[PDB]
């Protein structure tokens, strides 16, 4: 997260860190056994880390649970990032409480101009590299489809939306991938891609979760 703020410990209780010996992506807890992330975050060996603030210090509220199964979207295209969504099933159920909690799936898609909360442990610089230990947050508005398509001509599908600031300076970034975009208490986006981070006229691009709710529900009900 570039240009954001320190969230505060466990104030984003649905945020997870995906670990393969090191933090590599975010995710969102949607019930006690399932996490939603980005398909481009797929790795063979994944441990889900819930209740994290500092990802390099055991502070007392963590749950570390290995994945039993990953399910990349059937239509995921790694070239275009169309359908950049994956479900991860936990080997054992998380214990839900104040610091570890699920985020609701959307019934409606999100509205242009809604300010959403984007969070993660990704790079905090638009040029250079600095990775935080504690969870970072950003308030960012949903941009119109027209503005998004103008920013990334020939690249935005119906399964993507832009959020952030055309002036630059505030955005998600590498290492935030797979994490949440929460708008009005619903998971509306997944950190997916962008040209650099926090660059002028190059806002973040996010997987449009409202298009996948039927797939998510059907998949959870059968696995
Ligand atoms: Ca920790
Ligand atoms: Na809704």
Image (spheres, helix red, strand yellow):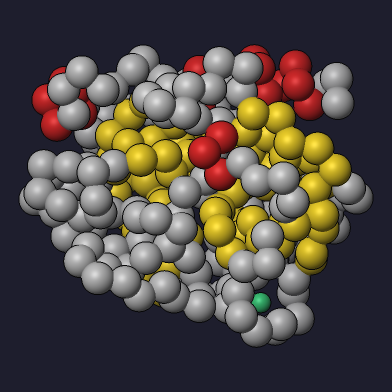
Q: Position of residue 84 (x, y in %)?
A: 50, 30
Ligand 1 falls in quadrant: bottom right
Q: Residue at x 23, y 43 (%)?
A: 195
Q: Residue furthest right?
A: 92
Classify 36 as above or below 139: above
Give the answer, above or below, for where 167 lies relative to 194: below
Q: Can you see residue 184?
A: no
Q: Residue at x 14, y 31 (%)?
A: 151
Percent position of residue 176, x then y: 45, 55
Q: Is residue 36 visible?
A: yes
In the drawing, does residue 134 fall left or right of residue 141? right
Instruction: Look at 74% across and 36% down and name the residue there.
Output: 70
**Quarter the C terminus occupies:** top right
Quarter occupied by the N terminus = bottom left
Tell me: residue 36, above or below residue 134.
Answer: above
Q: Is residue 206 left or right of residue 37?
A: left
Question: Percent position (x, y) of residue 11?
Answer: 56, 66
- Name the residue at 48% across, 65% down: 121
**Which quarter of the figure has residue 189?**
top left
Instruction: Tell me if 109 is positioned left or right of 63 in this view.
Output: left
Q: Could you tell me residue 15's position as x and y percent?
A: 59, 56
Exactly how many numbered labels are in the figure? 0
> Does residue 127 appear to the left or right of 17 in the view shown?
left
Q: Nearer the viewer, residue 87 or 139?
A: 87
């Amino acid at each position: 997260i570039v240009g954001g703020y320190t969230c505060g410990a466990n104030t984003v209780p649905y945020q997870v860190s995906l670990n393969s010996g090191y933090h590599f992506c975010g995710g969102s807890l949607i019930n006690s056994q399932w996490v939603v992330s980005a398909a481009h975050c797929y790795k063979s060996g994944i441990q889900v880390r819930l209740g994290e603030d500092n990802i390099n210090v055991v502070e007392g509220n963590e749950q570390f649970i290995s994945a039993s199964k990953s399910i990349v979207h059937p239509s995921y295209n790694s070239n275009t990032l169309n359908n950049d969504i994956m479900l991860i099933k936990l080997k054992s159920a998380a214990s839900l409480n104040s610091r570890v909690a699920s985020i609701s799936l959307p019934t409606s898609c999100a509205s242009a101009g809604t300010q959403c909360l984007i969070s993660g442990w990704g790079n905090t610089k638009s040029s250079g590299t600095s990775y935080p230990d504690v969870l970072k947050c950003l308030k960012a508005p949903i941009l119109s489809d027209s503005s998004c398509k103008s920013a990334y001509p020939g690249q935005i599908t119906s399964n993507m939306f832009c959020a952030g600031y055309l002036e630059g300076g505030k955005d998600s970034c590498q290492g935030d991938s797979g994490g949440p975009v929460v708008c009005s208490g619903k998971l509306q986006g997944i950190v997916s891609w962008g040209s650099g981070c926090a660059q002028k006229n190059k806002p973040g691009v996010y997987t449009k979760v409202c298009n996948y709710v039927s797939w998510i529900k059907q998949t959870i009900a059968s696995n």
